[PDB]
Length: 307
Image 1 (tube, helix red, strand yellow):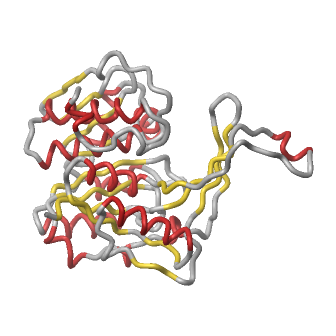
Image 2 (image 1 turned 120 degrees about the vertical axis):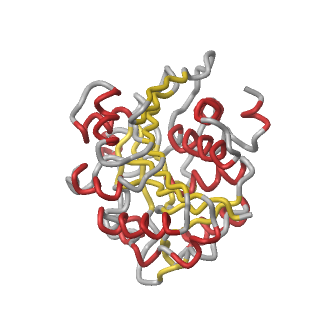
């Protein structure tokens, strides 16, 4: 039953919207609502993949506090295995405060000493790798301590157990470079970089050469989501384009990448071909964007096959 192991920081988000610098001009500024939600690429993937029908275990680091319990309760409700996810009394679970302006954009106030930054190789339960079929590193660069060297060790353990290795990415937090993770990337079977960010990291404009940079490090398959025209898939022996499902407006895009990866992964586990995986990924992403929040759209699976 355990199909996937998701490694990544599980955190809590608190969006303040709509706000602007003017909030500093009064003693008390009222909003229509202030609420906290579980967040983080890892938690989102574990949630969506579980809903799609595949048992998932989450490996992360959280504090022994209310935010941490909120995360554990979420996991319990979603049937996400948390045996490996332990609580650390010396740290505060990361609480990310989002400042969302009238334009819809947003900046963040974060805890530099939060759980997300403390996550490291000690939080990876290698003994459990033999229990799953696929490993998803939910965001290379997200937790700086999981650097190239740590990622290489993690992936070496994963491949020793024949696991499929999938990895997403975010923009480097400490000026890390592609060269610093090139070795670890040689172990990745499916890489899901984001177009914009991938452009910065590689310094290339075309999807093709951008993909080439990753293939150059040993990545087997590069799957680039191209918001609007589906996704661009590249390998050393082929290039494939699978247009996004047409007819979708979509209110919000946060978590789009997470739902995309979750759908692709669910498809992989079911043994579908690359085209079928891309279609499922695009379909899952399409449903997620129609609702507000990263995991509100995709409630089960019927909704996705419905497309």
